[PDB]
Amino acid sequence: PWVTIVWDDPVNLMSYVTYVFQKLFGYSEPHATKLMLQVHNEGKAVVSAGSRESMEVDVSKLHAAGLWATMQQDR
Ligand SMILES: C[C@H](NC(=O)[C@@H](N)Cc1ccccc1)C(=O)O
Ligand SMILES: [Mg+2]
Ligand code: NI
């Protein structure tokens, strides 16, 4: 299994990131906000998990929204 990681960046608005997580993944507002704050406070956070092919899509969707996203195998 793989995971998609979003990395903190100095340009994107906190409010925008919360919205992007809801729009792209259907997450609730408390869930999206929690992930956004984890990124901002820890520098990164797993935002989704699944097969390598599934995470490839999530990364591409996040890049199109302007967020710093990568994927890696889950240990
Ligand atoms: C402009 C400022 N944005 C931020 O401080 C960034 N770092 C917030 C963020 C959170 C998660 C991922 C990427 C960026 C703001 O006032 O919102
Ligand atoms: Mg980012
Ligand atoms: Ni910040």
Image (cartoon, rainbow, N blue to C red):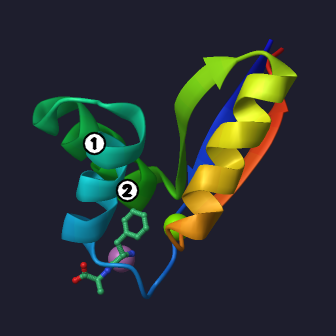
- Residue at figure coordinates x 40%, y 34% from the top left: 25
Asked whether disc 2 touches disc 1, contact meaning CB atoms under 8 Å apart, the reply is: no
Residue 57, x across and y down, in percent: 70, 40
Can the viewer see residue 68? no
Alpha-carbon distance for marks 2 and 1? 19 Å
Residue type highlighted by circle 1: Gln
Helix, strand, or loop for circle 2?
helix
Residue type highlighted by circle 2: Asn
Looking at the image, is 74 positioned above or below residue 60? above
Looking at the image, is 19 positioned above or below residue 54? below
- Which residue occupies the foreground of this view, 34 or 22? 22
- Which residue occupies the foreground of this view, 44 or 55? 55
Question: Mark 2 vs ligand 1: CB under 8 Å?
Answer: no
In the image: residue 71, left or right of residue 44: right
| N-terminal label among 2 and 1 | 1
Give the labeled residue for mark 1. Answer: 22
- Farthest left residue in view: 30
In the image: residue 42, left or right of residue 40: right
Give the labeled residue for mark 2. Answer: 41
User: How crowded is the residue under tag 2: few (<14 C-alpha within 10 Å), some, or many (20+)?
Assistant: few
Looking at the image, is 44 positioned above or below residue 71? below
Quadrant hosting ligand 1: bottom left
User: How crowded is the residue under tag 1: few (<14 C-alpha within 10 Å), some, or many (20+)?
Assistant: some
Residue 56, x across and y down, in percent: 78, 39
- Residue at figure coordinates x 34%, y 55% from the top left: 20
Q: Quadrant of residue 68?
A: bottom right
